Image (cartoon, coloured by chain):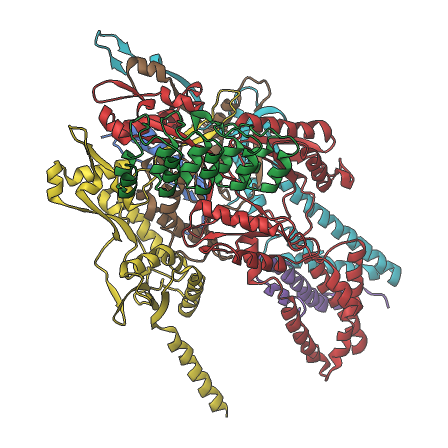
Chain colours: A green, B yellow, C brown, D cyan, E blue, F red, G purple
Amino acid sequence: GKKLLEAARAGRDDEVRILMANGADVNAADVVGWTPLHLAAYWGHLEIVEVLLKNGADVNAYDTLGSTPLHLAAHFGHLEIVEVLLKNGADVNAKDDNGITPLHLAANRGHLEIVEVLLKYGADVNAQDKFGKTAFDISINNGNEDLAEILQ
Amino acid sequence: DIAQVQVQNKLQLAMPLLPQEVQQQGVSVEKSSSSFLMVVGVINTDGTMTQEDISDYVAANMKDAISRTSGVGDVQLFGSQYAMRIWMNPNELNKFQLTPVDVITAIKAQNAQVAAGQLGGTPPVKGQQLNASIIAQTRLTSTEEFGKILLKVNQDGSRVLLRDVAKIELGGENYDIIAEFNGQPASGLGIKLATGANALDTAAAIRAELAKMEPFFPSGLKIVYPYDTTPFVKISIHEVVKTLVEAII
Amino acid sequence: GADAKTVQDTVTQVIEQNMNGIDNLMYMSSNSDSTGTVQITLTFESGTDADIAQVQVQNKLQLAMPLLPQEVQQQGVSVEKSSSSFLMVVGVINTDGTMTQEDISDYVAANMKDAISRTSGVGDVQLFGSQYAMRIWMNPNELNKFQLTP
Amino acid sequence: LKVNQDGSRVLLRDVAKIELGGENYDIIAEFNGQPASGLGIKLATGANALDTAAAIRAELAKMEPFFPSGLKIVYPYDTTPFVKISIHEVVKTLVEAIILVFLVMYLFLQNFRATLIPTIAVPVVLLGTFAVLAAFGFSINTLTMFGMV
Amino acid sequence: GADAKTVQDTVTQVIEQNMNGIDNLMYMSSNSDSTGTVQITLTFESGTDA
Amino acid sequence: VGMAYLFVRLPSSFLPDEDQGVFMTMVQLPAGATQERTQKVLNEVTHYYLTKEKNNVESVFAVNGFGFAGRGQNTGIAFVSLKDWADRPGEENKVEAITMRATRAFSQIKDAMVFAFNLPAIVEGFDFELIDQAGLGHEKLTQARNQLLAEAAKHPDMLTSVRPNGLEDTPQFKIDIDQEKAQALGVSINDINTTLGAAWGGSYVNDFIDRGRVKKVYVMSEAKYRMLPDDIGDWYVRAADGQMVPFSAFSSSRWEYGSPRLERYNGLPSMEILGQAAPGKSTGEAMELMEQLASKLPTGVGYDWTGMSYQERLSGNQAPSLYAISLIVVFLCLAALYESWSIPFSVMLVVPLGVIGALLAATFRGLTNDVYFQVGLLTTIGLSAKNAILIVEF
Amino acid sequence: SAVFVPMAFFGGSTGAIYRQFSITIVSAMALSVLVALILTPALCATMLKP
């Protein structure tokens, strides 16, 4: 029944559609904590996300270590997905066990568009991770002039 | 074959008395004739690629293949495969109170690939559900990533990064070998023969080994054959065959 | 204890790249699994004595050896001219039960397996278990208590 | 490990746990549902298979007298008796073929004496073949032996 | 400067154990004297190119 | 022409896949699967053999952890001996059937790929590679293969089963050692990385002698203290001021995916593929479709054939050439005695007369054009050649 | 021999296998002729009944 997990894994949007419509647990969590929304936000499939969100799949669901699907989307540069999760009520300052926000995380792998979208939905450009770095800080240290100047 | 083994296995009678610096650079025993069967170059038509680009490209995605093919003793590369190059400044180093030793040590430490183990590894406590690998550090892949290596945190808190006192660029492993074709810049494969090899057959293999490459070439990059023994021999036998026929006449 | 990417990049590649100018090879398949193991098979144009085929390969393994980590070379690296199919498999068991599994494995490894391994025609005798080892099993708390590390 | 400031000593057994164990714990084998290990033996290319096994039972035949109590060998996977049997079957087809030939010979020439002639001539040919294919480096295999029928 | 037991256990054995899957050997005699020297002779089924 | 038709229709095998009196079984579990679970599945299989095929199976030897794909917790393998051929008459008691039934049952096992098979008459269909030529990297080649396999699926007629041979990407635990913190707290990166490795991976220290014989000394964490992600923080490392620091203080972790079994083919990254020509259809066409399926993929991705696939390239059918030279060296070598023009041709006509029975006697017992049928043909034609020769010569 | 010695000419492991048969029967047959040509006439000439 929790094949939905791997449905989100391998893509196959229309089997997710068959499965969601015959009553499979939409919030089913796997051995690592990762839901089908996590999986989709990692492997970057929008439509899977839609079919999941509209059916009321938790959007602020967390795995072990407290990583949000907004975390995953924020890192991998899935700019399309991050906007849809945000419109669906995704906590922008959510923190994994290590103090990391989606803003920090996006700020670190060099996605300028996504740091913008996160700031538009009212991120905190001051949130501090466990080691006390801001998204701004991890731009100076990356030598990235652009984020730093943007993150004023 | 055996001539070769005898030699290299006692090279390994000697190996642990040669310096670390030389053995880590490697030592090779090759059963090679002395005379390039051919030489193939490559060039960019557009100029959109510098010389060192061409050299790298060949070395990094052409030369391994051609090197493996039989009859081939040592393929000489007219240029170098890239390398991460740190170019050091004595003054800047001195300013921060550093030596090349601290740079080298830092690079070894922060460009490391570390064995980290597993979650749930055997022998495990019964009832374990999760079995996973731990990842620690990976070798760095980018000039940028080498940039943000941390040399030291100053007494006041501030950090000194490697890019602050050194200069990082992708470059040749050596800068001694500079080749040029028809007055425009180039690299190539100088191919030697392995003693006892079949010459035309080896080349016949080399055009094969190489014929699979072009579709994945970047824009503007084209092969060219400035030195080639074979058509001499195709012609040498063409001429004799024709003397034979006309003799029969 | 190495992941697949580590073992790919730190061992497997520093071997492949050093595979050059050896005779008669058709190709070089290369799996690099996450259990910290490499296996690189070179297959040679059929009817080419395995003996010299073998030497060419392993002596340039020793073109590469001093660039592989200490941890891996001290674990050893092997070149074996092996067909792919077990001619036989012989097991051993205790009838009484007076010997656990690991005992049996050790016994075989420690006093049976060397002999059988030497005999000719034999590529790599696989041992279904392990030879013993002195095992130190560590406790983080106790270590910390006395202020110690591994 | 260390002598404490007060004089007392910390020994390795005080903070670690020592036992004899496998080098790895990944490989666990079992035979007929009771626990076991074994030798998975591969071939070295170009090897002589039956001869290699013939050597392996030798290599191993010297071991049993020094086994500890209760420990016994067992052969769960073995290619050889297939080949002993594969050649047994062909040899028996050959003999019975020689018979059947001798019957069609009698039934046609209707004389004990006549039938000796072609009968004697067959073995001479067929073993004669071993001689010549030995001299070309070919073995008495499944295929070859089967070809001669 | 190594005793015979040292040279047996630290050198001689770490060689013998690594002797496997080599062709045609009849046996492996192995003296390990206290002068810090090892000698391991492998003798091969006669008529096997050295 | 009866010959030409009955010939061109007859199927072609290599050698008969005989009852070797032994066979093999595959136990392959999903991702992040553990030893215990596999052990379960192995017991289910072993159970089947010992309980249900008592009459045939003689002994199961089964191993958790020795995959033939290669090692894992999530892999096992059972070597099966059978009872003598004498003591199990009947197809139903022969290997092929045994494997069939076995598979049929094991299919019931959820959460695992288990099936059983005979090892082919060659002790030592296709094998298609997929090369990362332009250095596009593992997740992009993943995508390349995903696209290829799930676009092949759209040709049931042409290709019957296109599957990857490797293992799939699986969760793994990333730790990032804060370098800045490490330096601040005066704790050496060597000490850190060693502690991590020795505790969690295990470390080979040095050798000892066990009853006259050298063996290893391994240091590693007790199981309970390395079984879970939160156990990571429990480990302390000593800094230069003699003060203990937990891993939590200077590390940070997060989950990601990645392949537990990478591959390379000729020094370039590749991922391998298995498949075969659908029923009735030739290997050559199956390969040709795969060849052009590949062409519609991302740039930098290419392909190569290996093993059996590679071989079938050199040549698969020379029979029409070398039987042709057989036919001319025969047209003339006969005349080397008949000393006659065209007289051998008369004997030659009879060649198809013989092969007709051969061809049908295979087709009715449902047999195949294999090495044995071939060599068969040669002997039969040669015999009917003799008979016809002697007639025309007399 | 002119029908099957050619079948020794197949390349690959296919032809590897074909080699055995291809030659084994030419050997068997050629001597079969030489012996039938020497022995059988002798044995015919001597052991048959007039």
Horizontal arrangement in the rendering, residue F275 relative to residue B200 (left or right): right
Residue D37 percent across, percent down from the top left = 54, 28
Q: Quadrant of residue A116?
A: top left
Residue situated in front as seen by the camera: D102 or F150: F150
Horizontal arrangement in the rendering, residue B231 relative to residue F14 (left or right): left
Residue B57 percent across, percent down from the top left = 34, 57
Q: Quadrant of residue F181?
A: top left
Residue situated in front as seen by the camera: G16 or A46: A46
Residue situated in front as seen by the camera: B118 or E9: B118
Q: Quadrant of residue E22?
A: top left
Q: Residue at x 66, y 66 (%)?
A: G4
- Number of numbered callouts drawn: 0
Residue situated in front as seen by the camera: F143 or B196: F143
Q: Residue at x 55, y 62 (%)?
A: F314
Horizontal arrangement in the rendering, residue F306 relative to residue A23 (left or right): left
Image height of A27 relative to F155, above or below:
above
Image height of C8 relative to A36, above or below:
below
Residue at the extreme bottom of the image, as rendered = B249
- In the picture, the quarter occupied by the N terminus of chain B is bottom left
Query: Does residue F29 appear in this view?
Result: no
Residue C16 percent across, percent down from the top left = 39, 49
Query: Does residue F327 appear in this view?
Result: yes
Residue A112 percent across, percent down from the top left = 35, 42
